[PDB]
Image (cartoon, rainbow, N blue to C red; front, top):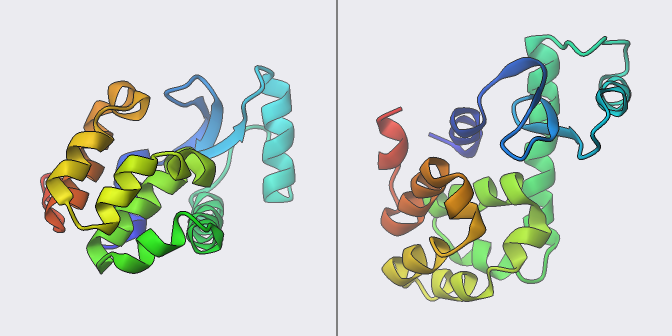
Length: 164
């Protein structure tokens, strides 16, 4: 299992504009379009993102393309970020996927503020980290997805996604 499949599970696939858990206009596999309330602003962003008049609808291939771009961005964001890079470098390949997942979901910026957890992760205090991660708005808002990522950091296996 890799970070692409993991995110495909957590985000779903939706071919028509929809609102995400925060009420923002999204399309595809968790591709945020605009935090603006206008359906018009969204469709506009959408069209600029795809390079065609989509009228609020995209194909599977278009969704997968957006997805690869967003994944690449999360990865490149971790590697460029002074707080995130050292953690990521310290992790094994499975836990690396978990960090990527957080970054895709909440942005570089958001993840970089979980200072305490990042430090635990680097020190490989898995249990302590799992506990600190859970005390967040993130966990309270999207508890099932957050448990899945937290278990991945805790055990270093794909158990939480093998169910699914």
